[PDB]
Image: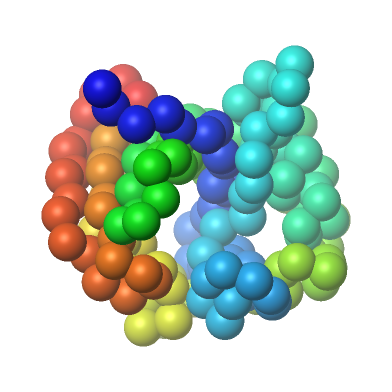
Length: 157
């Protein structure tokens, strides 16, 4: 059987000229920039968990997000997969503020800091910028090494 998986969200604030990323401050993946997100909680829809995580980690409150992708992560030595649902929005009305877990920062869209993001981001982030939807899977050894991955553009997430 396929391993069991745990539901996570990942949220990108994407405006015409810039994207909001957050630096993970502690723990696994510390020092890397990426979307805001976390585990979906009991009795919570995936979109509402994504809205909750955006607010908890960045302070930004938005009323709705667009579902743009799904990425499954597998790590050598850990039988449980991460099932990550990726959301995007262009419309905010507050200021991003540093939380205990994340430091938000804007990057211009010709200065996307790929060298400081998770390696999988190099493959699916360009699809998001093109307003495409995607399904992906990545198997990691540790934090740096991809041993296998699949990626496909889809019409519906």
